[PDB]
Image 1 (spheres, each protein chain N blue to C red):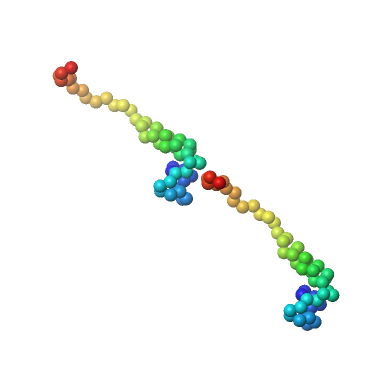
Image 2: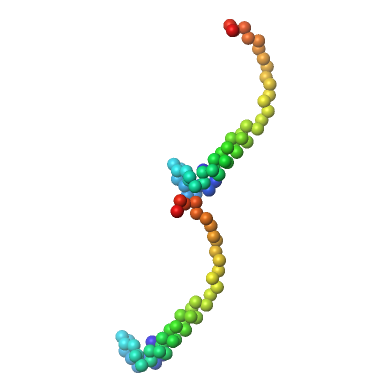
Length: 50
Length: 50
């Protein structure tokens, strides 16, 4: 319910007519919520079995 | 009962001998009442399935 839904839609509903746009925005938020660098951390040598 | 009817006929009658004039005046009022400009308004789309 990112756009074109608030103000008339019910909490339990979604509007199929505006599906693609809302899906697009949700994916966009998913993408933006991951823009970060993969820092390296400390390491330990393992001695456990295989 | 615009003309020729003020104090000549009863409140429940209409003058049959002055019909043309009264009709003409009534139409004239009808015409003058519609002298307006059809202004625009806020157009919008509907997200409804209809």
